[PDB]
Amino acid sequence: ITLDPEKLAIVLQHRFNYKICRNCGARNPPDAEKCRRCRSRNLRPKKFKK
Amino acid sequence: GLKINRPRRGSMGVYPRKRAADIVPRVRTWPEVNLGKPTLLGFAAYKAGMLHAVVVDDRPTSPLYGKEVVKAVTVLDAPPLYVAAVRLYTLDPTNGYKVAVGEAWVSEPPADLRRVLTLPEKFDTEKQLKALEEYRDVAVDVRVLVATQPRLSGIGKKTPEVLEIPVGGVPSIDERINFAISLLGKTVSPKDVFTPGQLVDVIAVTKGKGYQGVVKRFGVTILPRWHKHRKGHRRTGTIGPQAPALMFTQPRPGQMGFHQRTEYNKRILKIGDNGAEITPKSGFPHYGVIKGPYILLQGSVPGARKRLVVLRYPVRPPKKAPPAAEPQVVWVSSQS
Amino acid sequence: ARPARCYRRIKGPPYTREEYIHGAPMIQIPKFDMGTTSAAARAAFTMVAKLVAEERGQIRMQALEAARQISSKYLTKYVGDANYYLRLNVVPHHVLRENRMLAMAGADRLQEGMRLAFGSPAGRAARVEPGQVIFYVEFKPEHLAHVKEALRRAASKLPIPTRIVVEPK
Amino acid sequence: MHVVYAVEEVPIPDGVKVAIEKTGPFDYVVKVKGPLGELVKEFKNTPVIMSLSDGKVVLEVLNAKKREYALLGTYKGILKNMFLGVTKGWRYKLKVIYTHFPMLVKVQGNQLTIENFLGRKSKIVLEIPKGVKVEVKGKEDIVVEGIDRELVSQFAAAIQAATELRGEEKPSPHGREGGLGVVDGIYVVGYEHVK
Amino acid sequence: KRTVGVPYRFHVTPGIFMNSLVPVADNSGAKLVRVIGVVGHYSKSVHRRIPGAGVGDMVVVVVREGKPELRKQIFRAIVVRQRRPYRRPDGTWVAFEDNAVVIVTPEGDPKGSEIHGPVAMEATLRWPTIANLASIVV
RNA sequence: CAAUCUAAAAGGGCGUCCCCCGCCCAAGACAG
RNA sequence: ACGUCGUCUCUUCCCAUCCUGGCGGUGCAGCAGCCGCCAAGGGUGGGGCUGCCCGCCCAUUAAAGGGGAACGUGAGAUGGGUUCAGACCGUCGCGAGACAGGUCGGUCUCUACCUGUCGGGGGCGCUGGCCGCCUGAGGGGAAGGUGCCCUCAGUACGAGAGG
Ligand SMILES: [Mg+2]
Ligand SMILES: [Mg+2]
Ligand SMILES: [Mg+2]
Ligand SMILES: [Mg+2]
Ligand SMILES: [Mg+2]
Ligand SMILES: [Mg+2]
Ligand SMILES: [Mg+2]
Ligand SMILES: [Mg+2]
Ligand SMILES: [Mg+2]
Ligand SMILES: [Mg+2]
Ligand SMILES: [Mg+2]
Ligand SMILES: [Mg+2]
Ligand SMILES: [Mg+2]
Ligand SMILES: [Mg+2]
Ligand SMILES: [Mg+2]
Ligand SMILES: [Mg+2]
Ligand SMILES: [Zn+2]
């Protein structure tokens, strides 16, 4: 599964550029410090591999 | 809770299982149908008996498509209905209730209607129609009052049954009113209402069975290893926990049958003009002979063998309508 | 061991005279002063953090030991043993008792229920007062964030609410 | 905190006529007309006082807390979108991305239909709201146009959402041992003005 | 892929049930089997109800009488004959003189190479491999 | 609007109202 | 003097959810699996063994969840165990006897007064009496639940196997 750089950048922004709250699982903005839903700071960034 | 899971015994959606308040079905729901012309949305007929027919399956996707299959059918004895009155309905602004605003009667009602009604010697129909017209602009629904003609049926009784049937088919209330007024004093035959091959709902009071025990009434099990049990086996073991006390959901003996029921999506196989072609040479058992029009329905219908049955346009029709062409009834078991 | 809530509150007199107590348990804390303990090198440290009790109560010996392990490990890893002094400030003098049916613990322990209810030794605890210092740290001001984190981890192991007070020496 | 009085001003651009109507004790209806059309927005149950001053919209709050004060910047931002909406319009651009099955996007009347998404036999059908124009540029790009930025952005978001599978149908975003997975869909890529 | 049978299974009054002893109608070695299970979307029952099967249904059986190396072994089989009268969807009422099953693999392929006696059309339509060996179909 | 009497902890939250301290900005601070 | 285990029968409630509905994460390629959240409308079955309960096991299955109701329900049943009087064994006791160790046998009472529940009747009222046709406040409902096959397609995915 291969995409040219222009489409790869779009896909990474939309599918791989956010955080997951370890406390409640909620999706959060990539630069957030607290979860939008439960206001926890236990946020994990979702990472694209390889 | 239960030691081993299983569904409850019998429905509580027909609670209370009392005798029907009336032997004539009282229909709560009438569908909104777009037929392109005004028409009655229902008909009333007498259940005559059951037969079976060889019908060609006309469902193209069906595994039996094009084959001859045997189907149990119910015969309805359907003399024309006599239209006696027209009633108009509006909505009460206080609560939104549908309320009758007036009605116009035929001037000379048939003598058999006097067996059930307190009528004047003559109705002054023109005044009643004039008064009715004043409520035209607030009308939301129009229904005709029809009387059966049991003398023309195989029962041969004289006292008719009277009920309201709405007029539908077009969304315009005014044309429905004009069509209903044109029907005053005339008869309506089954072919004026339905077309062969269409689906109908049927409403009737079911056959009466008297007082029945809990085994038959609710399907509770006979106590297993039946001979072991002192004080009988056709019973529940317990009649409840300690609390709450006897609940209304506990199965109990009582009246069984003689309830009003509605069944959906029964196909009309044939609407005949003369019942001699469908009446068995022995007659219909416990009913008699059919001399006028009849309706052949696919499947079974609630009610005993002389019950008045109301057919209406379906309120839960399936997504795919039946084929437009009339179904091919090759042979009926009452024939040679 | 029972849940620590069973021995949290101060419900009677201190029970510490080991010459009158048969089978008083041995203290299971190996060291109480960690890091750089020599007074000469402690003169380099100029800050003091304290984990201070907020309520009165009894802290079991194993909770003090669990708190001591997590904080000292954190400081050893992130600050370095030459750059801090950590002292567990309270000693578990009080002996805890339990009334349970047991064998090889005396004939009276074989009677069930509340008959002869005085318990056999079950552990040790420190009786602390509000404002009492549980842990005491001496460190250099550059490591303030790390010392606060170490004491936050220690507090999560303790049965009573505490608070961290940072002051200069 | 607490605000005794705070005011904000939004300058009305040339050719734009703004009417403010009080439809209730704290309700407003703001009608904005420009060369490209007329927008109507409702501000209901609001503490912001809305008024016109010789070519500006004046927004004020009195005796306000943080909750009420925060609405001045919001209403200024909404009004600015309305002014640009009737003078320059809004264009949201979408990109069609597929891995193996090429999507077929077409506009039929007021229906937008996407076919062959991931080789599915089902057809994604969306209803195009009044005031929104959708044009398919080539096979890769979709453009949504209009004067109501909220309406245009919401529809563009709906197209993207329609291609995001959920529940048991959601594909793995990453491939075996960590590469790109099955990432097919329509993605909003940016916005700009018509003019 | 393999040849497909008909997608439908109309209601049939079941003829055999758990612990029924049924003769085998093939040359696979087994002669008499005990029914110990019903397989498929129609096997589910309710409290106290014993699961049962009719012509065309697949069952789980244990060889009771037969060759020594098959005794006490668990197999799958298809009901091909049934004494219990049943109504076909076209309305015909059918009954056989005896009950019979045919040993198959879980995918429906017969173990033996020949089927003895008549075979109900329900069995042959649902299982094309059985239709191949059925000399007489009714 | 105390108790009998039907309740709640460790912990998390600038969610919101408020108090104090340290530092930057002397319009060359924070954000792009 | 509140009938002592279990089971049968029958009803309802809880949710800390086994399946079915929705969503998310994954060390989620696919097929599967694992983990969290909402959700109690419906389902949660058939057998072997034991007096059981529990548990182990067999063939299925979408799955074959767990709890409460005077350890729901013996004036409803059953009576296998436990737990009377007879008897045998082992052990203990000088003895008569004892053992919550094993074992064989061993009466399950009542015409329902009140209430409840289920169905069936008589009357009075409804602003003078009556007939017929209607309305619909509220009340009940699980009236429906849930699988399989073909096509999609040996396709997407994958090195292949598989799918
Ligand atoms: Mg008996
Ligand atoms: Mg005390
Ligand atoms: Mg507490
Ligand atoms: Mg008493
Ligand atoms: Mg009692
Ligand atoms: Mg008593
Ligand atoms: Mg829950
Ligand atoms: Mg009990
Ligand atoms: Mg009894
Ligand atoms: Mg009792
Ligand atoms: Mg006994
Ligand atoms: Mg016995
Ligand atoms: Mg005994
Ligand atoms: Mg002796
Ligand atoms: Mg009695
Ligand atoms: Mg309701
Ligand atoms: Zn969160």
Image: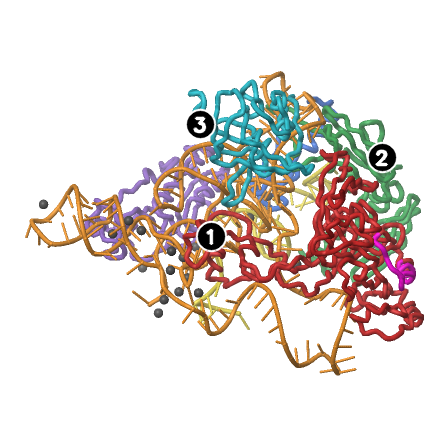
Chain colours: A blue, B red, C purple, D green, E cyan, F yellow, G orange
| Residue on which the image places disc 3 | E64
Estimate how packed mark 2 is, as few (under 14), some (14 to 19) or many (20 or more) residues with alpha carbons within 10 Å. Answer: some
* Mark 3, secondary structure of its residue: strand
Provide the residue span drawn in magenta: B176-190
| Residue on which the image places disc 2 | D107
Q: Is residue C40 left or right of residue B1?
A: left
Q: CA distance from mark 1 to mark 2?
A: 68 Å
Q: Are marks 3 and 1 in contact (CB under 8 Å)?
A: no
Image quadrant in which you'd find residue B290? bottom right
Q: Is residue E93 left or right of residue C134?
A: right
Q: Report the front residue among G70 and B315.
A: B315
Q: Report the front residue among B40 and D193.
A: B40
* Mark 2, secondary structure of its residue: strand
In the rendered structure, the residue with mark 1 lies on which chain?
B
Q: Report the front residue among C88 and B211.
A: B211
Give amino acid for label 3: Arg
| B323, above or below A5, in the image | below
Q: Image point 79% across, 43% down: which residue?
A: B321
